[PDB]
Structures are given as C-alpha cells and as structure tokens.
Amino acid sequence: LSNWQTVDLQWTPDSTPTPVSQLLHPTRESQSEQEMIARMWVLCAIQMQEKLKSATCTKPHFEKYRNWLASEYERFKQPGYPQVPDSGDLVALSDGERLKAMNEMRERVKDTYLWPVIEGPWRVYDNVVDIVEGRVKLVKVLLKDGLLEKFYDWANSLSEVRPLINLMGRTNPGLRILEIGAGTGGTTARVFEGLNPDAGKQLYSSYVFTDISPLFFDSAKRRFEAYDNVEYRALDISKDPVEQGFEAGAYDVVIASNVLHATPCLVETLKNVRTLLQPKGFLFNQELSPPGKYVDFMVGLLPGWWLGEADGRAGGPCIPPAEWDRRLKQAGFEGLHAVGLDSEPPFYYNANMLARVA
Ligand SMILES: Nc1ncnc2c1ncn2[C@@H]1O[C@H](CSCC[C@H](N)C(=O)O)[C@@H](O)[C@H]1O
C-alpha cells in the first residue's frame, strides 16, 4: 500500500499532501471482537451442518451455500483456522453444549455495539431451513429489531473517516456530495459528523442520499432529521445516472460503502460514478476485503453473493485494494489515491479508498 499513503485534494492553491494515516485510520484495536465474531459464526456454521443437509435447497445458490459451508466446516477440523485456533474444540462440543456456548455469546454482547454481529449469525443458523426452503427471506430475518442498521454501524465503527471528510469540507465549504447505496445510513452518519464540526457550521451545500431502493428513505429521513440540505433520491449505479435524472459532473465527492461490489460489472459502475463527478472530484469507496469468511457466512444465502465470475470476481464479489486500483484505472480514475485499512493487516474488514478522476 506504499504508493497510497497521502491525500492531496488539489482543490485550492493551498494544497499540501497529508499522510493518509491522519485522515483514514482504524478507530481501535479490534482483534478481540473479530475473534469473538469468528468464534460465533464458526459455532453457528457447525450447528448448521445437519440442518442444511436434511433441508430442501430450493434455489441453485442455496445449494452453493450448503456446499461452500460444508467445505468450510472441513476447515474447522484442521489446525490453525484463521482467528479460531480452537475451531477443532468447537466441533468436539456436543450439539447441546454448542447451543450453550452460542447463547452465552449472545448474552455477553446484549446491550453493546457487538449485539448485531453476534445475533446476526445466530439468526442465520436459527432460520436457515426456512430460508433455503423459501418460507422466509434472509433480509427480513436480518431486519428484525434493527439488526441490519446496527450491523453496518459496527462495521463503520472500525474506521475513522471524519478527518478526511472534514478536510474536504473545510477545503470546499460548499461541497456537493452524493452517496451511492447509502441504505441504513451507517456511513452517512459518520460523514455528516465530519461535515458538521460545530453547531452552526455546515461544510457542504448539498448532500444527495441515494440508494437503489427507495424503501430506505423514510427511516433515513428520521435518522438525519437534524441535518439541513439533504435530498433522498433513488439511483442504480450500475446504469447511466444522467438517464436516471442526475446531472453529469455536478458533484465534488461521491461516497460509497459496501455497495459497489454488489453491482455486476465494477468498471461500468465506476464509469457511472465518474460521470457524476466534476473534473477534480473524488470517489471515497469503503469496501470489504477481509481474509476470513464472516461475510460469506452472513450474506451467502443471497443470490447476489454468487455473482462475480463474469466480472473477473470468481472467488466472490469483494476485492482487495490492488484490484480496485486496476479497475479504477479502466474507468477513468487515476487509480487509487489513498488507502487506509480499518485494522492493521492482515485481519482487517474494510479498505477506505480515495480515488481521483483522471
Ligand atoms: N446497483 C445499485 N445501485 C445503488 N445502490 C445499490 C445497488 N445495489 C445495491 N445497492 C444498495 O447498496 C446497499 C448495500 S448495503 C451496504 C451498507 C449501506 N451503505 C448501509 O450503511 O446501510 C443497500 O442499501 C442496497 O440497496
């Protein structure tokens, strides 16, 4: 990552490169909670094996998940499973003792920020048959009691991105910002804090909150009721934004957290982001590329997790920064500009990437 260690916005003659470590960095050491998470989803995954095998996988991708999960379960019975070196002892527990351990982990994290990342995998285990047999949707399962929003709050909690946002806003106090696939608003919430440093100071002219799904807009209008000059408009970034009613080149910063990898073709997606940006504009792209399989476990029951092979992403939709750099160059960006991980490698979750229009 040594070529992407500084940020130089070049929006005013004032511009001096700033070390990325002051602008995008981890908020804390996170190995304990990451190993708590890994431990939990490994326990659920073990507990799912017999349930999955007797279940009727009603769609091809449910079969892919069952097959994938069976192969990962074989990895638990080998030494040195990443972040779970005692995975073998978890396989060695009785079914009843494993249920006891899973419920102890839920009880431990109740009323903490870690609640969604422990409860989430439990719910996947607890509903898997109803899900693969087409009686309940995964997303509905994860929506209950606000878990999805709190889950994305957890992921965002690992990255400190407010100094970068603050620098952009102090540099351009009329910042025109658009966020792709803002969803529950986990990243929107951090970004506004960087744009609102003090009462009576708003370092942006306009925040366009977008998602492909307008179903998010009511709750996000509640969540961000305190902020002025926010719009809420649908947008599919896999398709031309101008034809969808957006103005080409009318934005200084485009924000995207863990949405771009959900699109079928990253280069076309990045070209659509570039269409929105002014000639000196920036994409700030927060994107998973952890080495472990917690995200595979959590969202593998969705058909979209199995796209990627026609887009050079056979192993799954998430790619590390070197791959983003490649595809940014193919889309008219200067490759990556700066990158900061939400943890010291190799056990990080999100790469926080800034890319400039070429
Ligand atoms: N093609 C597309 N264009 C725009 N948004 C999309 C999209 N495909 C998926 N999305 C949206 O991207 C989001 C991915 S979930 C990622 C976390 C989210 N930013 C949050 O904080 O809630 C979802 O809300 C999804 O509806």
Image (cartoon, rainbow, N blue to C red):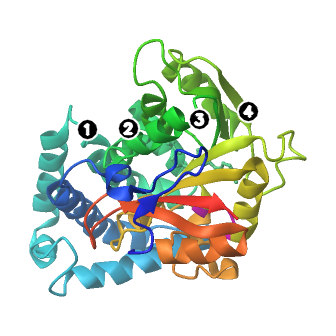
Left or right: where 96 falls relative to 330: left
Q: CB under 8 Å between callouts 2 and 4? A: no
Tell me the quarter of the picture where residue 174 sits: top right
The residue type indicated by label 3 comes to Asn
**x 24%, y 57%: residue:** 37
Q: Position of residue 21 (x, y in %)?
A: 32, 56
The residue type indicated by label 4 comes to Arg
**x 66%, y 74%: residue:** 329
The residue nearer to you, when weighing 68 against 114, is 114
**x 51%, y 80%: residue:** 315
Res. 180 visible in picture = no
Secondary structure beneath dot 2 equals helix
Closer to the chain start, of discs 1 and 3, is 1
* The stretch drawn in magenta includes residue 243: no
Q: Which residue is mark 2?
A: 150
Q: Quarter of the image for the N terminus: give it.
A: bottom left
**x 45%, y 80%: residue:** 67
Mark 4 Cα shell of 10 Å, populated few (<14), some (14-19), many (≥20) = some
